[PDB]
Length: 242
Length: 12
Ligand SMILES: CCC(CC)(c1ccc(OC[C@@H](O)CO)cc1)c1ccc(OC[C@H](O)C(C)(C)C)cc1
Image (cartoon, rainbow over all chains, first blue to last red; front, top):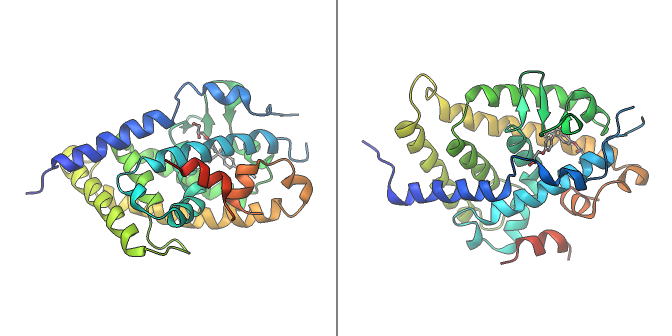
């Protein structure tokens, strides 16, 4: 009979507040991004570049708060963030994604984003199709907020990211997180929702590796032309590559 | 050297 210990309730309380401090459900800062343009050879590039950039900053802010992440070397902190960022952004975007019309609704019509907007940032269906698919199936899981923050933290603290030096340290942090999530589903997620829930969550992480790869490929294609690359941000260029 | 901005956002 496994129970949620003091330490695990602590972990969940930390990740919740970490999330609360880094996700603004009023989407108030959006007014500062270069404006959206819907008429267009890549008319959404500057607005979504800015949105991703912002998102990167908030993902870093959440990552810093993960129990044990601070114990990592600054070089592994960097490796974990560079390789996970797009993945965590896809997961956190789920919170604003609506099955109503397969779009991301950030408060208002100007900041409601759909398939044609991502198209206009220079992405093709090779990515968008399995991206909506992902959002749809992650939405259907109906995670408790607790499961959502833990899935994001588990994604960031992955031992097999290329370039990891203290793999064994990354593993003990992540295992302490898996264990908290597994035990959590058991104690707090009632059936039929709880059924295979963990395995389905872990499967969304595998789906993320594939989306990551395809995002990277099209980002490398986008940033071929120094003219597109001009319209990104310094943080995007540093984190996604140059 | 070569991730200044990311490094700075990570700092305590
Ligand atoms: C618009 C949909 C989506 C879905 C993950 C997206 C949706 C919402 C996002 O932020 C919401 C929260 O962070 C705010 O608190 C961030 C991203 C996306 C964006 C940009 C995008 O591509 C942009 C492109 O990669 C480039 C070149 C601009 C970086 C692809 C998908």
